[PDB]
Image (cartoon, rainbow, N blue to C red):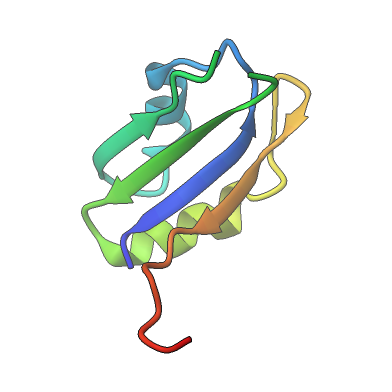
Length: 82
């Protein structure tokens, strides 16, 4: 409920890029940036404040970063039922 996925990232994306863009909505607790070696990277960002993760989706989904339209979605944990 604090975490988002960021996909369609440019391959030259750095941890600092994620930090600089996504800290604008609120304090970031943790970041994973894939060491994908292919066409696009992905990131997993956890916010300290739950409200900020929703803000990040609202503000950065479909945001262009180096010509790439970012996909920013909620990282929802596994549901209980099949």
